[PDB]
Length: 155
View 1 (spheres, rainbow, N blue to C red):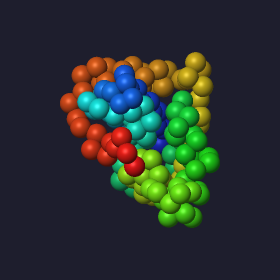
View 2: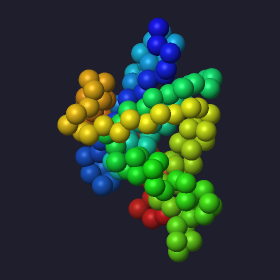
View 3: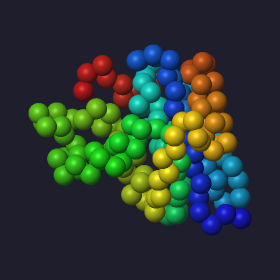
View 4: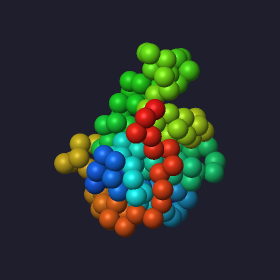
């Protein structure tokens, strides 16, 4: 068995907004949980966020995670933004709530319960689990059943 929890995530969206969905694979305990869902109206950014969210909300105890994703909006949030948003009380420079604060606060709550190592893969050099995620991702966007509540044309 594996000593570290492994998570692979991916999001897709056909429009902006449009139908999109996610693919997430997590190796926890001795199983391979596979997650995927399509949303009728949403964005690429929100699906790449959701990928990462459902995977972590799966962990019921504090674990050491290694999360691998080709998502730059997530990388960006994680390496540049989130730290500042917390300081700023989840607001932008002109004092408005940031875009997708609903999803970033949600991922934030989840990240906070674990020890996370991030692996940022280039879309053309992912691991087989990353490819299967994209595949799951695309399938879902194609047959969406859920509503992405938190979507705002607005802010």
